[PDB]
Length: 140
Image (cartoon, rainbow, N blue to C red):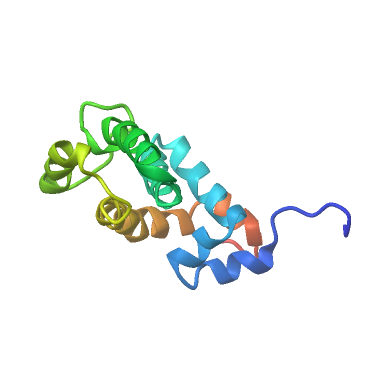
């Protein structure tokens, strides 16, 4: 189907190359998140995203707004989308929530970005959502 075509098996095989590769592409990322959503873990990827976008913020306002939100969202533990972060990273931000910058969150993003790439990614590779992408003529 030239007109309509979604989810290509050619990109999947490549996605495996590296975690980043998968993210780079929308399809790959989306699918990856789905797997987590079912396990109520998406919260992790949710933070990773807000970051990549946070940097694309304009002016101090956007940085402050997004910062406060994302902070009391993932950063903080008493939050719903609270992700697994280092004590310091959580504290430093809590106090530096007023002096946040574009090159500040970057640190936190790295923490999570890895957490997933470690398990999330691997586990995702063996996830139905992923497999389907290729739907190899042989299971196992």
